[PDB]
Amino acid sequence: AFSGILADADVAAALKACEAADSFNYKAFFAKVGLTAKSADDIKKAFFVIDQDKSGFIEEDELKLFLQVFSAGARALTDAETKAFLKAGDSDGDGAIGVDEWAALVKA
Amino acid sequence: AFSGILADADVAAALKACEAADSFNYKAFFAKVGLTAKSADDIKKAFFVIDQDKSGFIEEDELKLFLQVFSAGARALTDAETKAFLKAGDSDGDGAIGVDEWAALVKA
Ligand SMILES: [Ca+2]
Ligand SMILES: [Ca+2]
Ligand SMILES: [Ca+2]
Ligand SMILES: [Ca+2]
Image (cartoon, rainbow over all chains, first blue to last red; front, top):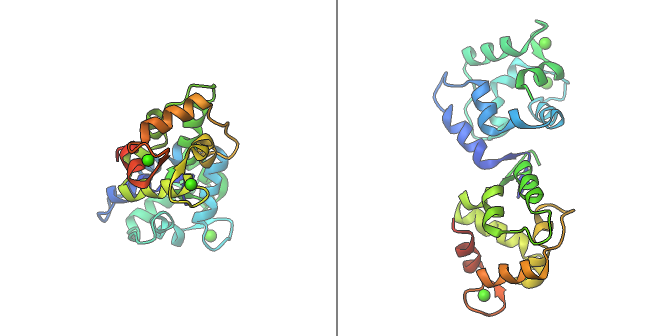
């Protein structure tokens, strides 16, 4: 696509910055790709893309492949990275990230 | 699209900045949308999008609707704006902008 919510270049840069195992930080990633500066609706659209199986929730397994949703050839997040990511977003402790938790997590 | 060469937000901002008749400046527009920082291939892809009729050249009439290629609801450039734009890019004086002239015009 010629134009989209996020610029391919920013996605590439955000991905490059966290290539090393255990170098991922969601705030840094969101900042670099430009998601933090988007509208609540755009943030929600990102939620649907990450929710690969359309269960209406982002499960730990989808966090593991979080980078791939942005860049198909990206690595999988390590268990430490996925667990920290889940802990950060899972306000209600149910083991997954719902739409409002996602919106709250991105802060936009 | 979730991701693209240019970010919708940057396109919106570049368009907003030149809403007034005769306020357009191609360098400012290219800078704001992020095209100046892209690869020669990405710059060429932009060329194809502007070349609406696929003649392999950007004619004055396509410069007039330049903004619309980026944002469908945008205004048409005034004759003064289109003429200045054409003069700037048309190195060989043939009345149109070819692919190399476009690449040279964007400077990327
Ligand atoms: Ca899911
Ligand atoms: Ca939850
Ligand atoms: Ca043409
Ligand atoms: Ca020419």
